Length: 303
Image (cartoon, rainbow, N blue to C red; front, side):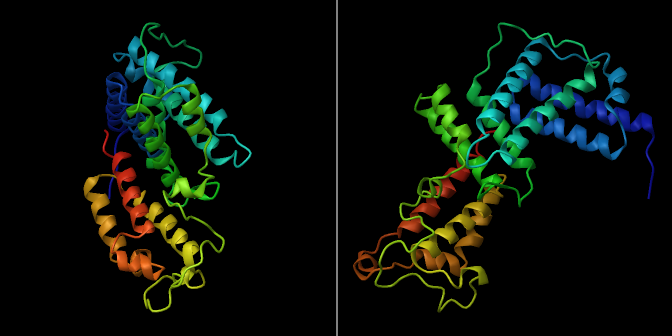
């Protein structure tokens, strides 16, 4: 087991920084943040500081275009941080977005002394929505699997917001008001969040065959005392969370195959009324699950 020189670690930090700058230059926001994050992780592990790396970057430059993107990123992040501070919740999401700012600042501080001014190209424009999606993608990548914003898993909420912003992009309805609604949302409306009209934590609808965990040997213990629409709501929520761990197309297909093999999925797929079972259509909850797979696919088919 084994040692590395300071020279050698600085040379690798220089490469990590270059990779970040290169992503910055191409306008790949999530790629830049991720690359910044790797630089920080590597430097922390080798006990290297920004001022150790700075002299070594003397032959490298953040372009004017680069500083313009970083200024837009800074602005979008500050604004998002404020917008995410809400009556429902104001600690986690703002903390996460302001930390994205601190990560970018770290990339800048490797190159610039404490008071040096950024020199952004004033003509270079970058769409607010591409920035926000990038921020959200980075937060989704880096937040702990157990992180929660209000009552919802953080990775899942990010994918939800990224899909909402992408829908605004596709239908040409992106403006400050529609972005604000997304940035300030915590998924308070459960039925929209899960894409399931009958989402509830209460008794929901009357059913001749109210969904039940009895007759499913393998169902997790947490569901055993839930029934009906509420049972399905809880299964869908946990499925949404598991789907949010997907990182690429192969990963998503694998997770989907796992979830569809579970007794919880058969509960979703089992109709709760006799007329409905005789029709031979997908249940509403299975439909919701399929929409979540599509949402997750869109939040991940991008970079």
